[PDB]
Length: 112
Length: 114
Image 1 (tube, rainbow over the protein chains, first blue to last red):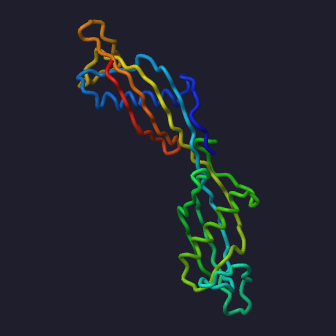
Image 2 (cartoon, chains in turn yellow, purple):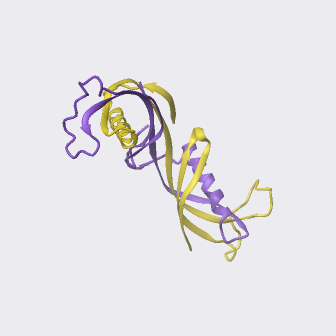
Image 3 (cartoon, chains in turn orange, cyan):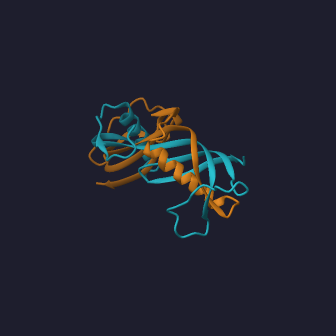
């Protein structure tokens, strides 16, 4: 899921880590000879953006439809013992709903 | 959400698995040596997992300490007590964090010397 900016307690470890890190990046680039530190966090918000990794192990069959034909209404698996083909695969899909997207991060397949 | 957890088994009834499946079979056919379309004969196992990414927006007033940047020991860094040396600064940092991968980067920052 997703969740627009919301106030966070300054005690939250995540905020502590984020603060240090930023005060880190700051001293690393500040035009001063002296190291600076947080005097006061006046405001602290967080937003959680998320994703789902799906791992599906799947068995596939060869159908009758063709990669040419648009009519993918119905495609039985094959009839005759010599046209039927079959593969096993471990797909790994990275989705992130609201962004409306999917990625076949990794696909491993064995034919037999 | 769950920042970082192991992968658990989902029900093969989930819309999410259902789609993730139809999607991979889709890419799968796209790349298969075969003039023929192929479909799931069966989904033998199906686990999911959740990558979480937290964005942080911190509003910070920074002060100038007594320690020097080229200093080894940084355990004691007082704020400047001498008027002509006191130096302040206001910023807004946006930090992106993927707890699992254990990383943070400064998406952006703005500071106004004050």
